[PDB]
Length: 202
Ligand code: FES
Ligand SMILES: [Mg+2]
Image (spheres, rainbow, N blue to C red):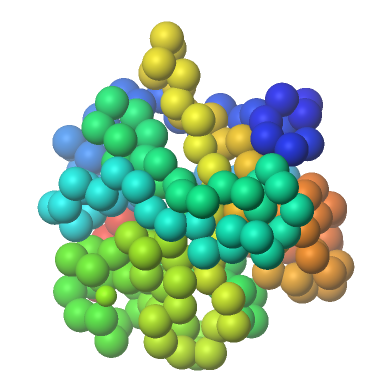
């Protein structure tokens, strides 16, 4: 379908109660999915469950870098009844390693997701993405922010939908130069999607 934003599909990720039940039962604030294509891993994250902070809006660092309307988004609002659910690509934009967002860590210098800071550290070359600052790079070699998956919460049903991205994912074999290039099939994208709940302490 093209019922998402600017030519993207509208894809149901999960119901809010699936996310909340997982957080209550396991403590795991990360929820993996694939979008817009089956081989493109992403994750939802409840930034308040993760950090203890009421994070309800983060910047779009790619404003004006791509055509509108996706390029015209200034900020990304958190979704659901608490306003705190966001989503990102799970593919590092340095060299395409899959990011271990499920490995919850207590130091900034450990690969994984540093919960207190909402910082996602790639094991391959040490890129660190500041999720609560819109995925911007705060350390390491990644040349641009981690792409955000734009979400829409259906208040009638509780369902959380993925509806676009603010940027192209990592370019592996096929160049991706616009968000909508995420709709291109690249056989080099062979990444799996972790089972939920996936979190571990690392
Ligand atoms: S592939 Fe992630 S830091 Fe290089
Ligand atoms: Mg930090």
